[PDB]
Image (cartoon, rainbow, N blue to C red; front, side, top):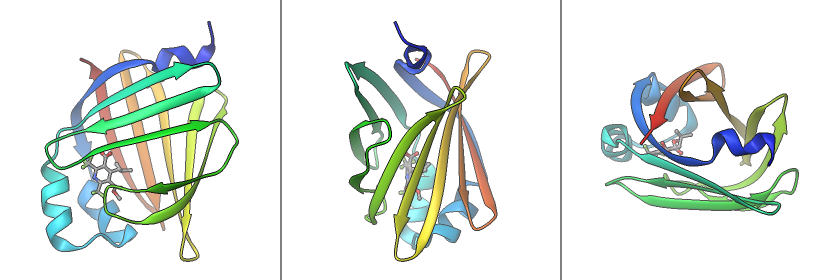
Length: 134
Ligand SMILES: COC(=O)c1c(C(F)F)nc(C(F)(F)F)c(C(=O)O)c1CC(C)C
């Protein structure tokens, strides 16, 4: 077992706040904001050895990343940014930093009660997206 295993499973989005504003700050265009903002993703998190896989599945896109904690990787995001990503596990929180074009956004994933809470930050704008087990 590992501490990280409280994230493993299949999660469904139950609430979102300020996601349109977060996407605007990231630079997402109008049409993608509208369709992606309507999405109700499931988040599938699995661990096999040192490799963590996180999939976001929705009517908009199916996206999947696999990574080792602390080891940078190239990621194509749902809005088609080509970013350099590093994910670490710091005090029980998965911290995902994406770098591109001299910009940075950080996505934190935390367990709180029976929720998995995703906090997304860009240039002072936060979105909070709350998931529960499927
Ligand atoms: C900048 O926004 C994104 O990168 C993004 C977009 C959007 F860019 F298209 N759409 C979606 C989804 F709702 F469509 F799934 C997600 C998501 O996984 O929730 C994300 C990831 C984000 C919550 C950190």
